Image (tube, rainbow, N blue to C red; front, side, top):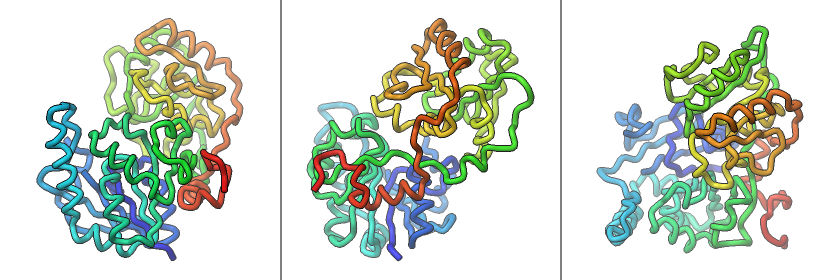
Length: 364
C-alpha cells in the first residue's frame, strides 16, 4: 500500500472540493494519504489547527502556517526580494513536511507554490515518484518569476507531469515526462443525477463561483422569462438585476448539484472575463459536469474550445448572450465527451506511462 503526499495551496478540509481533492479521495482509498497545505484566505476557519496534523476523511491534513509566505509582488524591481522570499520558504520546510516526504511512495505537487518543494522532495526521498498535477498553467496563476524558473529547472526530473489539458504543454519545458490526464468525474454521476429537483418548464443551471458574472443572468432572465435560471454556488446573493425567474441557491454539496445539472435543459459557465487560458475549455470542472450529461452549455467564446454543444457569447454583450442561449435551447443532448471517473483518472495521474494514450510527445 503506497503512501501519498499531496502538496498544494488548497487544504483538503476546505468545503467545495477542487480537482486535487477528488484525486486525493482516490489516493486515500489506495494508501496512507497526506495532504500538506502551502502558502483573506479560504483556509482561515482552519487557523486554530495550523501546524498540526488533523485527520479528515481518511487523509492526514496539515495546514502549514508561517508568518509570511512568498508571493508575486508583480513589481519587476522587487524580484530579488521575491526570489529571496521563495528561497527562504523553500529552505525552511517544517519537520512534518520532511517526515511526510520521507514516508511517501508518491508525492503529488499541484501546480503553483508546490513547485518550490520539488527539489526538496528529491533530496528527502529520491525513490519517491514525483507527480506534478498541472491543474493550472503557472502563468495563469501568475506565480512569481521564481516559481516559473524553478519549474523549468526541475520539470525534466519529475517522474510525471500530468497536464489537465494538452494546451498546457507549450509552457512546460520538458517532454519525455509530460502526459495528458484531464479531470475525472464521479463514478456515480448518473446515480446522483436524480430524482429531479425541477417541476415542469425550462430550467437552466449554473454552478460555481469562478469569475461569476451576474450580468449574464440579469440579461438572460429578462430575455427568457420562460426559462428558470438556477444559480448555484455563485459566491454571490440575489443580484438586484435578476428577474423573478432566477433562483439563487447557497453553496450546494457536489452530490446535490448533480440533479440540477442532469435535469436542466442547458447549463451555463458565466465567466465574466475572456482573459482566460486556452486550456480552461478542458480544465473547467463545471463544463465537464455538463459535458458528462451532454447538457448543452452557454459559456464565453474563450472557453467553448474544441467542444460541441457549447454556445459562445461575449461577456457584457447582451445580444451574444441571447443568441447563445437561443441555440443552447435547441441543441440536442449528446454525450460527446469521454469522461473517465476519478479512480481511472487517478490511475493515469500516477502511472501515465501504463496508459500510453496520455503521452504528449513521441512514445518509448
